[PDB]
Length: 299
Image 1 (tube, rainbow, N blue to C red):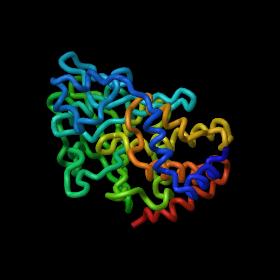
Image 2: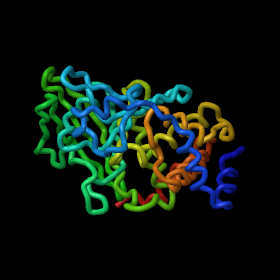
Image 3: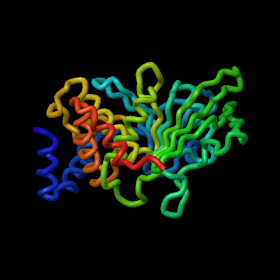
Image 4: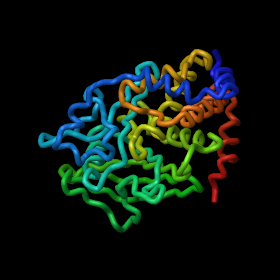
């Protein structure tokens, strides 16, 4: 069944909430014992969002290897992602340690530091070239090199230095700044334009470690990003849009981290993004230029 027709069936019958509840019911449940250890209580932003033991990222340190981060491994698509929470004031150093150890080239941030009047993430990267950050617990230094600000998203070029070895790497920070406080964006053009900017950078490519994706809890907006990317990749590999079942891909991803896609309107939005993205995958290259125009990214 073409997903565009499934989409109309669900929309016309008003059954998004019902489909979404079925997904919750069917989703995997695996233990998350390490997350719940008392020594780790101050490393978790939300009590009800934990990585499963089997897919958690381990820090390469002997004292405490725990970070609230999961490795999503999509075997058929041949793409991996690290999904993580917005770093806390005491875990910013752990965050950058993970980036270094996993050899990531890109960090995708889908939230603002302050949303709905409350703090959702620590300010974990430098805002001025001349004021670099030093993370003393993990022996890393971070410098802003350059920033490219567009209307609803910003790309930053960062240099991460391992102070123990003096090795350095370029990290790209992709910051989507215009996800609304409530609901989802009305059109996915801006979303897709951003996703293909991340792709074009090489950050999702197999020669690098997995991209790090986060929002506040690392399951909702972050899940929507990974779900759309994997679905479009699978349609690419097969050049067959009707083979790909978004609901099945989502349940597969939910084997690796709980709760991905937090609302029925994020699910609907995921279908819309994949449907519109398909036009490009199946060979209408000009659509990419239309997304840029519609996104009103400039100025």
